[PDB]
Image: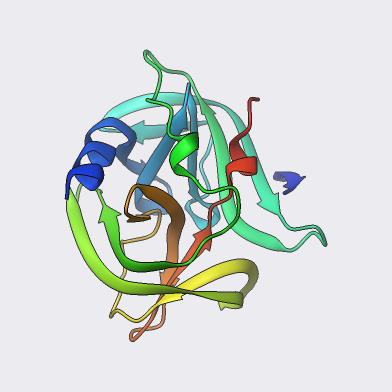
Length: 7
Length: 179
């Protein structure tokens, strides 16, 4: 599963 | 024009993942960015060279919605020229934008896409995306990751198109601030 980041 | 040509030489590379051929933008150091659907793996072919991907982070908006941008750290012998200053602070529209494409199958191309207008929500192939912009140009397959530029500004990454229109994910400087 992908590592996410709020941007 | 001059800016575009320089950008292609110093920052834009042909790439290949399990999802196909993509254009890739190197931003600074060993940090690069791809359309999310390119789905980089443990490794990627850059210019026919098998490079290690060390980190891969997918960008989402304040509410966790896809922005269609993947930021990768590369195992590389060199650093990308630093172009963060050519990326605006805020997602910006444009007048006579050039779409820079560079895959093994569509090498070193400059596509005149016209005006880039603020779009917003986009159903990209069934996946909801935010912070998109749009241009009226019959954009085709194999152009994803293409770099949208105008008068020295790097403003978007091509992510898709519906035949009459092309769509890019907007670029903000903040996406790329140090590590």
